[PDB]
Amino acid sequence: DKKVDLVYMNWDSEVASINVLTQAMKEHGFDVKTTALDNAVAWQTVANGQADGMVSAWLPNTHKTQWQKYGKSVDLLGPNLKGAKVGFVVPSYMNVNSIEDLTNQANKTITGIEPGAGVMAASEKTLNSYDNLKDWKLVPSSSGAMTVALGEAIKQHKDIVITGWSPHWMFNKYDLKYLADPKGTMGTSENINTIVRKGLKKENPEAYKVLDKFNWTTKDMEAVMLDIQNGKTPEEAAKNWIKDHQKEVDKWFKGS
């Protein structure tokens, strides 16, 4: 009679993690309910005990507002994935290795995404902080347009500098690298965390123990995300990843 009620928000990262955790918990005999909700709504359901938890708490910056409102009302168990970040990214075949080393590559353009995006604010700050970038231009478009442009550039061995972020399937599809950011204007890393309702440890110790132990890496998430980007259903992408990492998955369901 094991059960668990999980909520997530509909981002490609979370679709990957929530299907792996769902398929894993089903395989270990849980009745699993999962529902996608708006970000603020998902947090409130966990804070009020309407849902058992979420594995989609991005801290400290991305969900800063929600953590300020609800953090003291939930149990933060800890990180399930470490090292999410943003930065300038280039194909690995380009020589440059640091943002301070850019000069005239790629038509002095940073190929960006939606104008309102957090990586885009950081990119603007970055262009106004590094002396060598004074004549460079941030060109917004969309996430889809950026990845199309990345693909075409790599196909033709052309220079391109994009506003990249991780985890993301592009790092599995292509051979890319982040440019060093010695001034730190592209920010520091975040972790994705697990939060549960306060009554869980006592009322549902079976689910609590699993959520407490759930963890995987940026490369694992990127592998699942690439399968989905290539047409596999999230359920099949997840089952395939689980099969290949059975030892790692089984760890979430045993031990003190």
Image: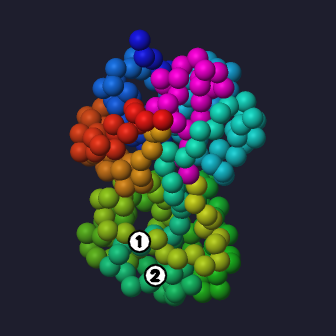
* 246 sits left or right of 159 in the view: left
Label 1: how many Cα within 10 Å (few below 14, some 14–19, many 20+): some
Residue placed most toward the observer, 12 or 244: 244
Q: Residue 251: where, in percent of width, then height?
A: 38, 39
Could you say which disc has been placed on residue 177 in the image?
1
Residue placed most toward the observer, 158 or 231: 231
Could you say which disc has been placed on residue 229 in the image?
none
The residue under label 2 is which amino acid type?
Asn
Q: The N terminus lies in which quarter of the figure?
A: top left
Answer above or below: position of 141 versus 107: above
Residue at x 50% of width, y 45% of height = 80
Residue placed most toward the observer, 203 or 181: 203
**Which of the 4 image quadrants contains residue 89?**
bottom left
Tell me which numbered mark, 1 or 2, is placed earlier along the sequence: 2
Q: Can residue 60 be seen in this snapshot? A: yes
Residue at x 59% of width, y 30% of height = 196
Residue at x 36% of width, y 73% of height = 91
Residue placed most toward the observer, 175 or 195: 195
Label 2: how many Cα within 10 Å (few below 14, some 14–19, many 20+): some
The residue under label 1 is which amino acid type?
Lys
Q: Residue 215: where, in percent of width, then height?
A: 45, 44
Q: Can residue 39 be seen in this snapshot? A: no
Question: Which residues lie in the magenta part?
Answer: 191-212
Q: Mark 1: which secondary structure?
A: strand
Q: Does the magenta portion include 145?
A: no
Q: Mark 2: which secondary structure?
A: loop
Q: Which residue is mark 2?
A: 97
Q: Residue furthest top?
A: 1
Q: Are marks 1 and 2 in contact (CB under 8 Å)?
A: yes
CA gap, disc 1 and disc 2: 8 Å
Q: Residue 105: where, in percent of width, then height?
A: 45, 83
Residue at x 30% of width, y 26% of height = 27
